[PDB]
Image (spheres, helix red, strand yellow):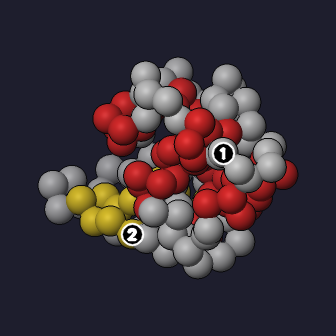
Amino acid sequence: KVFERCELARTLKRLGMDGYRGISLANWMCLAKWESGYNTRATNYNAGDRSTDYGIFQINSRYWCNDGKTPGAVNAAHLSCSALLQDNIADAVAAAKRVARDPQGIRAWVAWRNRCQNRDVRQYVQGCGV
């Protein structure tokens, strides 16, 4: 599923993402936008280390979800990576919260540093009623 901007903003608020571990809703929106374009079935294979990023938040198979084919893998979120390709984002949100629970926080996603950090991110949630 490809979410419309405001539709996603309201869904994330309802799922308790606004201000989670100090991360504003606008920051999660900025992340989803650059990671997947708000698409839940987006997948990205990293030929370099043989890992794959899954779903709306592009969660990596080496540490956060299990897909069986990633070398030297672990499963901190303890989820099947398949769960992160559903139209229902409940599981992807629970995984994203686990990632943010690590010391790096939102900085765990390099994309956030390149496209969101130290920028005006209000644009991602303006007009959405959140």
Left or right, residue 26 beside residue 65: right
In the rendered image, which residue does mark 2 sit on? 43
Quick one: which residue is furthest to the front in this view?
Answer: 127
What is the number of callouts on the image? 2
Q: Which mark is residue 126?
A: 1
Report the residue at 49% width, 45% height from top: 31
Figure check: 9 above or below 2: above
Occupied quadrant, residue 53: bottom left
Three-letter amino acid code at the position of disc 2: Thr
Where in the figure is residue 33, as x and y percent of width and height? 48, 54
Neighbours of disc 2 within 10 Å: few (<14), some (14-19), many (20+): many
Q: Which mark is residue 11?
A: none
Three-letter amino acid code at the position of disc 1: Gln
Figure check: 29 above or below 44: above
Residue 124 in view, yes or no: yes
Report the residue at 58% width, 78% height from top: 1
Report the residue at 73% width, 30% height from top: 19
Neighbours of disc 1 within 10 Å: few (<14), some (14-19), many (20+): few
Report the residue at 53% width, 63% height from top: 38
Estimate the spatial distance between the alpha carbons at disc 2 and disc 1, rounded to whole Å: 28 Å
Left or right, residue 29 beside residue 16: left
Q: Give whichever of 77, 44 is nearer the camera.
A: 44
